[PDB]
Every structure is written in structure tokens, then in C-alpha cells.
């Protein structure tokens, strides 16, 4: 059972930077003799083997055919905005609604992430984002890919949200 994590949000909010920081501290080699290299790289987060995908919808991915496929396949979603980019925060609701529509479910594991919290130019207050997360019923954390503040915790929290969802669906 790999946990399938998807990182979603506006262009330039730091999705790649966050994911690279996570992989750097959580990748391992795994022995697998049924593979014609005998070892593969895996990411292990809070004891779980995880797959990682980044969903962009702007830039080159404005020409993509894959947006809904990423939402169907992902099991939990890091919904990233940047604390110095009001429009990226306003975009979050559209991403969340789209995920709910594609997955046809109201309880989708998700964590709201306010990235670039090292920056002094802030236009999205912590309380604004906390209120949004509370309405959705999901955790909120502020992160910095530059300082590593919050990065591990954001992904660990998402893994726990997926775990609790899998435990519920099993029951
Ligand atoms: N100061 C600061 N810059 C960041 C942070 N995360 C990403 N960046 C910068 O923001 C820009 C976009 O980051 P990127 O990972 O390419 O965002 P993506 O388009 O969402 O994948 C790059 O210049 C990054 O170096 C952060 O936490 N703090």
C-alpha cells in the first residue's frame, strides 16, 4: 500500500521546492530482487511508503490533459498557497472544489499549507488561512522551503490524515 500524495496550488507557490526538501530527507534505497536493477528509491514518511506528485495547472500545464487524473489518483492533497501572494490563497477554494467534484466525496484527506513564511511581505494572515482550514475541517500549517520550517510536519500531517481515512474506509 503506497500512500499517494499530490501537491496542488498556483504556479510559483513553492510546490517543487517543498517536495524536493521532503525527498532529500526521506528517500531510502530498498532492496528488491524482482527488479532489473535490484534496488529502487522510495520515500518513507511516518513509517509509510509514499508516492509523490505535483499538480500544476498554469504554465506548460495549461496545455495538460491530466488535471482530473491527478485528482482521481491522489489519496491526499497538500493544498499550497504562498503567504505573500493573495491570489494564490484565493485560488485554493477552486482547487479544493475541483478535487471534491472529481473524487465525488466531501471527506478527502487534505492539508492547507501557507508556504514562504520566511518572507516579510505577508498579505495572507495566519488567521485568514486558519479560518479557511476550519471551514473545510482540515489541518493548516505554515511552511518555508527556504528555512525548512514546517515542511516535514506538513507532509507528516497529510500522511496521518490519509491513514485515518484508510482506517475509516476499512471499517
Ligand atoms: N523565500 C522563499 N522562497 C521560496 C519558498 N519556496 C519556494 N520559493 C521560491 O519560489 C519560487 C517558486 O518555487 P517553485 O518550487 O518553483 O514553485 P512551484 O511553481 O509551485 O513548483 C522559486 O524561486 C523558489 O526558490 C519559500 O518557502 N520561501
Image: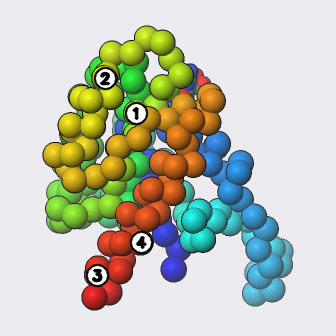
142 to 123, vertically: above or below? below
Residue at x-position 36% and y-position 77%: 166
Q: Which badge, 4 or 3, comes first in the chain's sequence?
A: 4
Outermost residue to the front:
127
Asked if the residues shown at circle 4 and circle 3 are in contact, with their CB atoms under 8 angstroms apart, the answer is: no
Badge number at residue 10: none
Q: Is residue 62 left or right of residue 95?
A: right
Q: Which residue is mark 4?
A: 163
The answer to whether any part of residue 125 appears in the image is yes
Asked if the residues shown at circle 2 and circle 1 are in contact, with their CB atoms under 8 angstroms apart, the answer is: no
Q: Which residue is mark 2?
A: 125
Q: Which badge, 2 or 1, comes first in the chain's sequence?
A: 1
Judge by depth and name the residue closer to the eye, 102 or 31.
Answer: 31
Kindly report which numbered mark, 2 or 1, lies closer to the viewer in this rendering: 2
Distance from Cα at disc 2 to Cα at disc 1: 10 Å
The answer to whether any part of residue 69 appears in the image is no
Badge number at residue 114: 1
Q: Which badge, 1 or 4, comes first in the chain's sequence?
A: 1
Q: Residue 155: give x, y in percent of width and height.
A: 50, 53
Q: Is residue 19 left or right of residue 132?
A: right
The local secondary structure at tag 1 comes to: strand
> In which quarter of the view is residue 157 placed?
bottom left
Q: Which badge, 3 or 2, comes first in the chain's sequence?
A: 2
The local secondary structure at tag 4 comes to: helix
60 to 109, vertically: above or below? above
Q: Residue 24: give x, y in percent of width and height.
A: 71, 48
Asked if the residues shown at circle 2 and circle 4 are in contact, with their CB atoms under 8 angstroms apart, the answer is: no
Distance from Cα at disc 3 to Cα at disc 2: 35 Å
Amino acid at each position: 500500500t503506497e500512500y499517494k500524495l499530490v501537491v496542488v496550488g498556483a504556479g510559483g507557490v513553492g510546490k517543487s521546492a517543498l517536495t524536493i526538501q521532503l525527498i532529500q530527507n526521506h528517500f531510502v534505497d530498498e532492496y528488491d530482487p524482482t527488479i532489473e536493477d535490484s534496488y529502487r528509491k522510495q520515500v518513507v514518511i511516518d513509517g509509510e511508503t509514499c508516492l509523490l506528485d505535483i499538480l500544476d495547472t498554469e504554465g506548460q500545464e495549461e496545455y495538460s490533459a491530466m488535471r482530473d487524473q491527478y485528482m482521481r489518483t491522489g489519496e491526499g492533497f497538500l493544498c499550497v498557497f504562498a503567504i505573500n501572494n493573495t491570489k494564490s490563497f484565493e485560488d485554493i477554494h477552486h482547487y479544493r472544489e475541483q478535487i471534491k467534484r472529481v473524487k465525488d466525496s466531501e471527506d478527502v484527506p487534505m492539508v492547507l499549507v501557507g508556504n514562504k513564511c520566511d518572507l516579510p511581505s505577508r498579505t495572507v494572515d495566519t488567521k485568514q488561512a486558519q479560518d479557511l482550514a476550519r471551514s473545510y475541517g482540515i489541518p493548516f500549517i505554515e511552511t518555508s522551503a527556504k528555512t525548512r520550517q514546517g515542511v516535514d510536519d506538513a507532509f507528516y500531517t497529510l500522511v496521518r490524515e490519509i491513514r485515518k481515512h484508510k482506517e475509516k474506509m476499512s471499517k
